[PDB]
Image 1 (cartoon, rainbow, N blue to C red):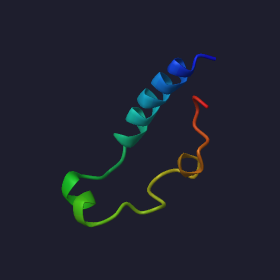
Image 2: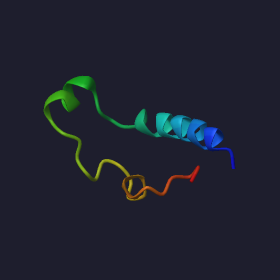
Image 3: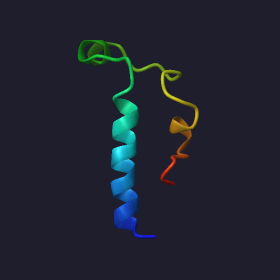
Image 4: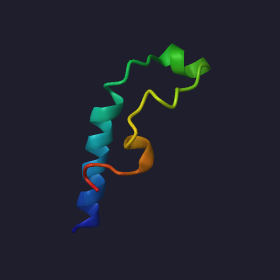
Length: 50
C-alpha cells in the first residue's frame, strides 16, 4: 500500500489509544508508567493498521 497512508493511519490510531489512559501530567512526571497499564498487543508491535 501507500506508506504515506500507513503512517497517517497509525498517528490517529495511537491518538485514540493513549488518550483513554487514566494518567495525568503530575503522575507521569515522577512515577513511571507501569508495564501492565497498556495492552499486551500494544507492547508487541501488532497494531490494527499493520
